[PDB]
Image 1 (cartoon, helix red, strand yellow):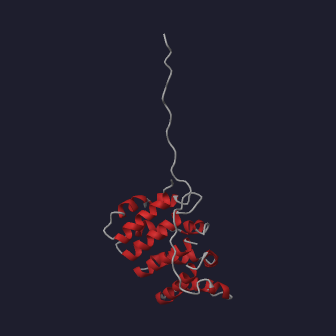
Image 2 (cartoon, one colour):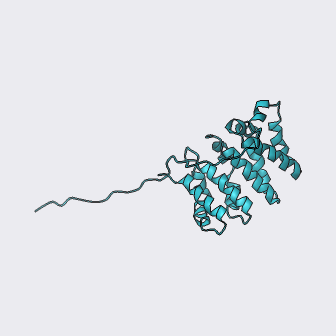
Image 3 (tube, rainbow over the protein chains, first blue to last red):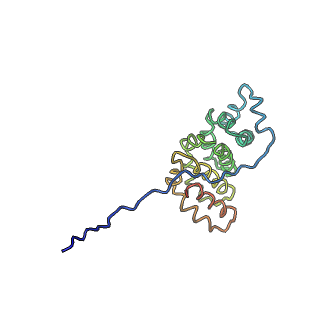
Length: 115
Length: 84
């Protein structure tokens, strides 16, 4: 008269979302990427992004280009422009019909994300 | 660096990405791939964003997408979600 007591009932469940970034690709040299931060300026960089809210695609793209130069510069630079509401800018302009503006927005925000 | 994603994720990376992760325009989708992967590789469970976006399945799918650029980076994006 044995008492067979071996109940296998365990909830085998754990999440697989640990700390892993696994690579970051950023190879670009526009020359002066850091230098413009050395210059600093009174408010060129916050202006660069303020320009992005204009109704002129060409002002957008030229300023976005300047953002991109800085955004691909480093963390020290991205956070300077992010602080001016840069995020708002590229995401709003994503609603533009101009599909090259979309990708450029993504490109610049990917730059800042890579900081 | 690290905590910039914290702001990007709040700004609304997903509203754009959820739509355009299916974009037929290479330049857009290939850019979106890095925009997604670069934020997904964050911390403080930053990777949740991809789950809410449901981009996981897109990635796996895009890995077999004829365009090799997307194909390669589509899997690169999974690397940011996974953890070994």
